[PDB]
Amino acid sequence: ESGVLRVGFTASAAFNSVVPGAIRTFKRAYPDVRLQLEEGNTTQLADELNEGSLDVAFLRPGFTGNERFQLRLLSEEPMVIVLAETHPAAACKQIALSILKDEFFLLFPREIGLSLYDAVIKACGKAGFEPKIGQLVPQISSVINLVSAEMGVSMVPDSMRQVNVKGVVYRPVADQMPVAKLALAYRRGDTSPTLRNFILKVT
Amino acid sequence: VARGESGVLRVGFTASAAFNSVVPGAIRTFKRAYPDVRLQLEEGNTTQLADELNEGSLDVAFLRPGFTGNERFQLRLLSEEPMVIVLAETHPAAACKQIALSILKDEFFLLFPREIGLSLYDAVIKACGKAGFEPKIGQLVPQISSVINLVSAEMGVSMVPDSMRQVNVKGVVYRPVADQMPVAKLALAYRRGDTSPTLRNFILKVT
Ligand SMILES: O=C(O)CCc1ccccc1
Ligand SMILES: [Cl-]
Ligand SMILES: [Cl-]
């Protein structure tokens, strides 16, 4: 219809084409709706849904509260490896996650950064080891730039390939099939026509 | 032994600054040539990084000059860099190789909170200010990366450093500004009189 709609997403989720593609499709079909967009991590985006300062969110499932919200599983992209071009393993078409047992891992801060981190370590432990914590920077951008500086490595969703930083390469892992999970989140009982049309343009 | 071969150096940099090739390049060079120093890297906006320099929780920073209180620190001006226009592929102005800023006087602009960004925000307003308008503030997001993803959603336009060409997001292109010459300055800030050897060797690898 027409009105306001507060849409949230994680910075890493925004690269996933389904996030700007849904905002594009909704902006075109309902150009009178006042869109108000927000960026934030999974837990903070959930607190806004609870309090009411947000209507729908592109977040990662598994957070503590997925029962009291309506969760629409969206897509599953694979997790690739960020490698410095100077690294000798960059020549490999596919990397065994086992090969990076002796490298530092630049990941999200262990605290509010609860998304993806837990997915890296779970896929990483399956290769039979636990990554030593390298540098902890709260943004994917700086994670990828810090790999360019030869400060370590990391695992990122395949949608991170759009960050074409000179000096880094993106290679999938052949040992396993790690994936990044995304979900559409909104409260269980919402009657907003402006919101309703959004889940319909997403799905 | 205490000649900078070993020890701890804390380096700071802003989000946008990291994309510039000087920041990563300097770090690897220092790392390569001084493996045994514990590098403690961290991100922050220029205001936060400078305060960390003054308070002693940070040894050197890659920040943007001009911030208030910068005369208290030693600033080595790094290489300047032009500011390009970001816009969706579907934008009709994307067909041009160079864009005039007066073209987008009513176009919604996708900027960032002035608190998270002082200089780049100032450069944007000052550029459009010379173009003869104040930018229609559309949405505000915290990381720059996110304005490029939001510009992919046709939610407006924005102006970012030329380093962000590396953000090759499907649906956005970058075209330089033709009617003016916006720029994005970068400096290396440290304490005037910090004689930490590890710090001094680091300045050598930057300049
Ligand atoms: O580099 C940035 O991320 C924005 C530039 C900036 C940020 C904060 C203060 C001055 C300049
Ligand atoms: Cl000096
Ligand atoms: Cl001086």
Image (cartoon, coloured by chain):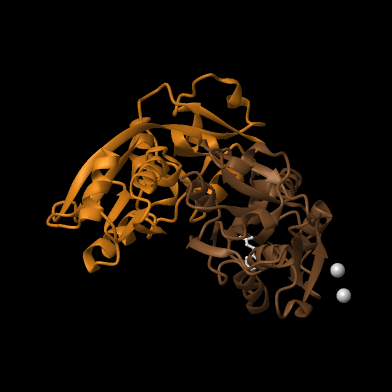
Chain colours: A orange, B brown
Q: Nearer the viewer, residue B144 or B9?
A: B144
Residue A101: % across, % down: 48, 34
Residue B182: % across, % down: 76, 58
Residue A183: % across, % down: 27, 43
Q: How many marks?
A: 0
Q: Residue at x 76, y 57 (%)?
A: B183
Quarter of the image for residue B58 reads: bottom right
Q: Nearer the viewer, residue B150 or A49?
A: B150
**Does residue B50 appear left or right of residue A18 in this picture?**
right
Q: Residue at x 77, y 72 (%)?
A: B194
Q: Residue at x 42, y 21 (%)?
A: A174
Residue B80: % across, % down: 80, 55
Q: Quadrant of the C terminus of chain B?
A: bottom right
Is residue A94 visible in the rendered structure shown here? yes
Q: Nearer the viewer, residue A11 or B51?
A: A11
Quarter of the image for residue B132 reads: bottom right
Is residue B167 visible in the rendered structure shown here? no
Ligand 1 visible in quadrant: bottom right
Q: Residue at x 80, y 53 (%)?
A: B206
**Does residue A101 appear left or right of residue A30 in this picture?**
right
Question: Relative to residue A147, is residue A4 depicted above or below?
Answer: below
Q: Residue furthest top?
A: A93
Quarter of the image for residue B66 reads: bottom right
Q: Quadrant of the N terminus of chain B?
A: bottom right
Question: Relative to residue A159, is residue B85 depicted above or below?
Answer: below
